[PDB]
Length: 75
Image (tube, rainbow, N blue to C red; front, side, top):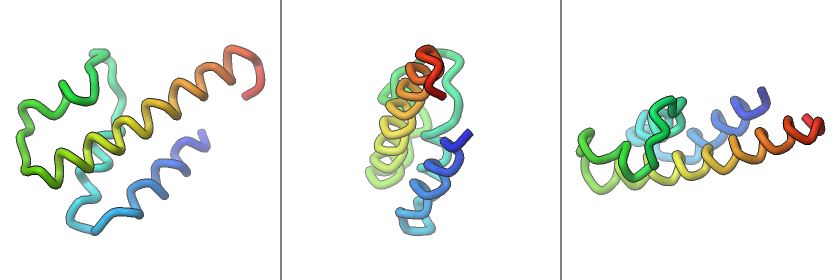
């Protein structure tokens, strides 16, 4: 989808040493965990967690918007 496009550009906005944190935050969520919950045991600093959390909340909203658009036959 064009969400891949929105993700690629989302990752690029961060310093290179924090990009993987953003990528991991935007992975699929089959266990239906909250973004906060998904940070609890990776336990990597204040920087990586914060980036993980932002990108997670970012992609989560995008997924819902895409789901609504698909449901309404707009996308």
